[PDB]
Length: 257
Ligand SMILES: [Hg+2]
Ligand SMILES: [Zn+2]
Image (cartoon, rainbow, N blue to C red; front, side, top):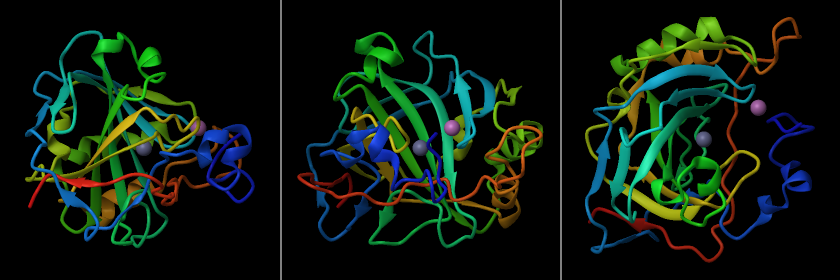
């Protein structure tokens, strides 16, 4: 199946998922000089105070921190969004070296990693129904750069040891996602898709301008995970990012002057 290697990586995805070459694929390069400030965007609202994390899973492509989304707890709203989107999981994409790993780019600059907080539109009732709609998802994207440590990330970092290989999971309750947010909520927004197969075009992307800093030691532990399952030949989990795709007929809007 799909992966990030030479025989099954992003250049191969289109054969099983033809939408890979579609009209609103993600990620994209964010050209700051073409993006336009949009005075019509309402303030963004990130309400994660009642968030309930449940588990962490190595799914063979990245690791997912999963949240109880059976009630309106952790929600994203305002900004370009209409209605309420509920947090279902977060995950990251990173590189083998600090000069690469993010999916979106900013004037071609690649960050060391990128965090995705995935949310689904509550008017569609469940995630699986939301991903059959053009406005079913909202993903909050946050860049990571290497510098000082991010305190809020350490509990994540500490448990990776226990989910080294594909298919392993650990209990991961009471984690507070607010500790992964930067100070500013200034963002760029555009309509796009999920960046892993099946690459569904159901997402309103909200990419924060301000990156968070994580330590070299923290990112280094991400690089010790495995894409393979227990007992198989070790293939480090690194470079699990899709590169920038064609912007096509899309405009990127800025929330800030
Ligand atoms: Hg996978
Ligand atoms: Zn992602």
